[PDB]
Image: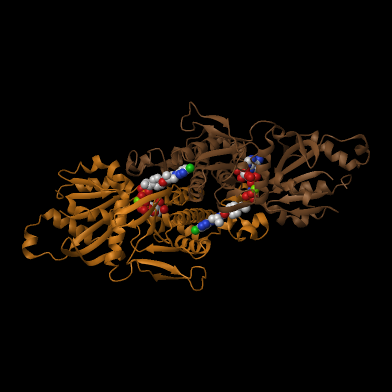
Chain colours: A orange, B brown
Amino acid sequence: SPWFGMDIGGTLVKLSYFEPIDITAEEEQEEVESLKSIRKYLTSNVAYGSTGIRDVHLELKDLTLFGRRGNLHFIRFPTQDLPTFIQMGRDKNFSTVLCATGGGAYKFEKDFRTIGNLHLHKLDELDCLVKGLLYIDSVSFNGQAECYYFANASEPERCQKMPFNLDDPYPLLVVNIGSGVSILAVHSKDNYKRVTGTSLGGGTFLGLCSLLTGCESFEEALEMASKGDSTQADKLVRDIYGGDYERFGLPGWAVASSFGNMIYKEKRESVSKEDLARATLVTITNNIGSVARMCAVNEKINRVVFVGNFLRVNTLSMKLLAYALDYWSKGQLKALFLEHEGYFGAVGALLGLPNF
Amino acid sequence: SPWFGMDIGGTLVKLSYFEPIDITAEEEQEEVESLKSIRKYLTSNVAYGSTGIRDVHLELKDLTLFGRRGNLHFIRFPTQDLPTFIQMGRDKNFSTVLCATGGGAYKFEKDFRTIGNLHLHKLDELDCLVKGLLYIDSVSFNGQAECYYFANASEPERCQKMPFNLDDPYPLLVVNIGSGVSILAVHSKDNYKRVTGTSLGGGTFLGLCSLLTGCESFEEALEMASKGDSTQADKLVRDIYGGDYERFGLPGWAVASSFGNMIYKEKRESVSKEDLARATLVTITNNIGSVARMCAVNEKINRVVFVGNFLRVNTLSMKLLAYALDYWSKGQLKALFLEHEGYFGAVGALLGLPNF
Ligand SMILES: Nc1ncnc2c1ncn2[C@@H]1O[C@H](COP(=O)(O)OP(=O)(O)NP(=O)(O)O)[C@@H](O)[C@H]1O
Ligand SMILES: Nc1ncnc2c1ncn2[C@@H]1O[C@H](COP(=O)(O)OP(=O)(O)NP(=O)(O)O)[C@@H](O)[C@H]1O
Ligand SMILES: C[C@@H]1CN(c2ccc(Cl)nn2)CCN1C(=O)Cc1ccc(C2CC2)cc1
Ligand SMILES: C[C@@H]1CN(c2ccc(Cl)nn2)CCN1C(=O)Cc1ccc(C2CC2)cc1
Ligand SMILES: [Mg+2]
Ligand SMILES: [Mg+2]
């Protein structure tokens, strides 16, 4: 049986697949054509159907897992297309213990059981996130750091991505930005809590963008936002005060009211779709950073790691988060990021396989 | 000189006016026609021009202030129309010490000084809020409680507005929902801090609503929202899990992703403008309640009072706030509201008049 871990989220399915590379001669005889066909299909394609993608650059090579050497692969596709995945799974010449997490492990349990003799084991979506994150960081990204930060995030001429060491990772605030946001306080390998969450997450960015701009993809939304000026939509401190609000240390450039200039008909008429995309991104990202900061201060944790796919190919939000956390905490908190940010739940699920 | 206090916000100007009612015979001789004309104009009209409104139901009658008996009046108009107000102020037969707060006391300082021999004294917008709130509560609302809560906010068949006693008001978390949000921790009459704020406030509700629905007023936006179903736009916990997320006590009805269903083209095509208005209101209100709760827990304050004009004629948001704070704090925090919620800064400004 192939070794998969699966995180079925509200928006995306993430799949970790361990490809053995130490297959012997007698081991290839004792394996069925369908097992060979699935291994060949997964490793010889980087697009699967019309919406599946293997993130080739994330592959972990020559990993020893469960006493075998192999490569760990990272694949994603829309949860909306899970029926197609399950149909392909029921197809002839494919007849497995599947560790699954995320909400969809429960919602689609009965659908996975249409695959004959498949054994589905549901695991908790935040327990899998924790052990996946700790595992990838422990094995490294092919010898490079899994974790990084933006050095000198206050100065743009200096702000550069730099590796960050998490060899003693506790305590840790994990901010999981998916469709919504979950915020976790990790005190040990076996001691963590969901301290809170927010419903203003990646799905809010994509949903509002689509309504406001007509964009048809996450990437198109980000490309619109990169061209925009959020201050066309947002009311700033200087629009209210005429400059800084000195008494409480609020700089004139801080957003006083997100989309607050859109109360004026003449401004709604002059704002561009790119401006609205950028205002949506800034609004969502700042609120996440602000909630993360309050949780860090309350939990007394100074390391905040942001994960989830809201941040993939999204350097705008990452830099905004890095700069904001540093500025508003007056340097007391650091924003940390992880190369495998969207996949930790899927890896954690795969790690539960020995328990079955 | 008439006794005014003025709070010039990013969206609305609030004006408190003290009308003396113990004017003697010899006092009426020694007063100028312009002073008489302004008193008559203010007390004989409830609409001023096309956008000024006197909130007659809020009037405090037979108040003793600065050793005089009179009535305290509450008037509001859009900051956008302040040029008209200043022009009327420069008009002949109107030729005052004006205590002003809010950002616009600084932004429009030079404009107020076009009124000859007017003396403008700027006061801080949150210091004025505190002393105004404490003062109105101390004098009562014509003998009724200024402060109220929604009893049994978890049960709708029982949930009713009830008076709340703030005779010993400290400590207190004050959540000021204007264009944006400021959150204050009040420990004594002279000891308070702005613990944080959020840029997702009343101007976000009105701005996003106008973009999403075409509504042209705050009241039209609220009326649209009252007819809508936010779950048409929002992705709920049960849309992701199929039911409750038991492990972390998240009910199926909780919003997992605000506007998160709008990532699907077919749902954007079926959602109504009323649904989007309601989703905007729920998103803004829940985020405010959530931020207020984190601040209360961190500050160790169990009384949270919500003020600002986002909540005027807005019982939907008030009940949402009451229910949410009670539910998510498991009954440890109570949402408190104030009858004069939009005007405390203007009253605080007026109270600074003796210092000049
Ligand atoms: N190709 C993509 N398609 C859709 N959303 C994308 C894509 N790439 C990035 N995103 C963003 O990533 C978010 C989904 O992140 P993800 O961590 O996979 O959440 P999820 O697990 O599907 N949801 P959840 O149930 O809340 O944990 C979306 O809301 C988008 O903001
Ligand atoms: N007639 C109205 N016109 C505009 N907004 C209204 C009106 N009635 C209620 N509101 C709401 O009340 C909000 C303004 O509240 P308010 O407390 O007066 O803020 P402000 O002082 O003008 N802004 P700020 O500079 O942040 O303190 C608006 O954003 C709307 O959500
Ligand atoms: C429980 C928290 C805090 N909520 C409030 C609301 C009002 C108040 Cl007064 N307090 N808290 C708002 C919603 N929440 C969330 O976690 C939303 C949420 C749930 C579930 C997910 C992921 C799918 C797992 C992602 C996101
Ligand atoms: C300083 C706070 C917190 N901000 C962040 C952002 C990122 C991070 Cl990481 N942390 N905090 C977001 C903005 N803020 C505000 O107060 C916004 C704000 C300013 C001013 C007003 C009123 C006009 C007085 C109303 C509202
Ligand atoms: Mg997820
Ligand atoms: Mg204000």
- Pick whichever, B329 or A229, lies toward us: B329
> In this rendering, is residue A165 above or below B153?
below
The residue sitting at the bottom extreme is A158
- Point out the residue furthest to the front here: B168
Residue B143 visible in the snapshot: yes
Q: Locate residue A112, reporting x and y percent.
A: 23, 44
Residue B188 vertical position relative to residue A301 in the rendered view, above or below = above
| Residue B352 point in image, percent of width and height | 74, 49
Using the image, determine if residue A17 lies above or below residue B146: below
**Extreme residue in the top direction:** B157
- Residue B180 seen in render: no
Which residue is painted at 76% across and 50% down in the image? B99
B338 or A161, which lies in front?
B338
Q: How many marks?
A: 0
Q: Nearer the viewer, residue B335 or A341?
A: B335
Query: In terms of image quadrants, where is residue B133?
Result: top right
Q: Position of residue A11 (x, y in %)?
A: 36, 49
- What percent of the width, then of the height, locates residue A76? 31, 55
Residue placed most toward the observer, A169 or A339: A169
Question: Image quarter for residue B149?
Answer: top right
**In the figure, is residue B255 to the left or right of B104?**
left
Above or below: residue A276 compared with residue A20: above
Q: Residue at x 55, y 37 (%)?
A: B318
